[PDB]
Length: 278
Ligand SMILES: CN(c1ncnc2[nH]ccc12)[C@H]1C[C@@H](NS(C)(=O)=O)C1
Image 1 (cartoon, protein in one colour):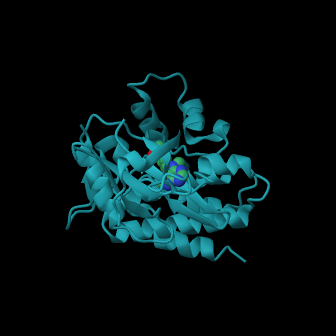
Image 2 (image 1 turned 90 degrees about the vertical axis):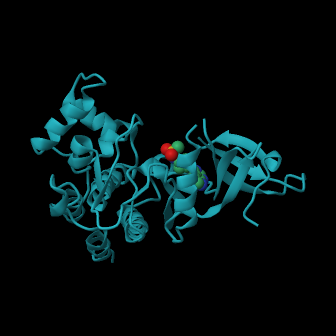
Image 3 (image 1 turned 135 degrees about the vertical axis):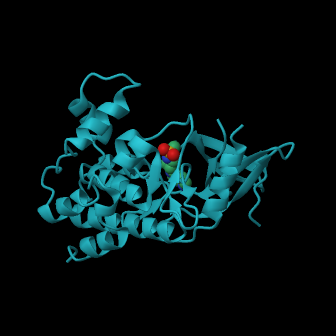
């Protein structure tokens, strides 16, 4: 009762590959809408993500629904619940009006809960950005993609990633950029950046990529990571968004301590934000 027949998954539109499908075995279009993750070779990677998501059960983590086999039973698809409001990246610009600071801080708490739960299971997300934070409702958010998530080996503080794959470098901590080492503290750094996005209502002009590119200047490509490391070494950071209170920025800056050991924890973040609400 967690297997989806590929012929029954009717594609609607791309979500991010991740596609919106309607699983409709009765053929009367009454079937339920679902998010489907497939390959655009790296079947072993998607199988790892499936094992990860099936093992996550939390209010602030997108629900695993099942798996769809691509014949001759040689391919796999990840089936997830579909949240129509989409990611913060698409939702926040559309609702700058109803979403105040209180609501943004509740989202920050929820992301931190989802991430702390992820941390307790010994995983590093390595891709925490607003595009990966889904809106269940105006009161609830969920971490919605685990495509770069890795399990930290027992008795180790981090996972080392040595591959030819792409990385969200404008969300990465110094240790990730310099040594390819990913700690729970590196996810804390990425949360800080995600929180910046959320506070700027995911305005494209104020995105971490747009701001850092304006700081770094004209840059290839192959030199982006070095220029970014240098900027972070000098102590430069994403500026406090307009009308962002000191208390929130101070928490945001604690996610951005150059050394991983000097950063705050997700639990200290939960408590910090919760103390600001009402
Ligand atoms: C937007 N989105 C989703 N939207 C609605 N309902 C969903 N259920 C699950 C995912 C999902 C996912 C595509 C992922 N983002 S990406 C391509 O940058 O990795 C997040």
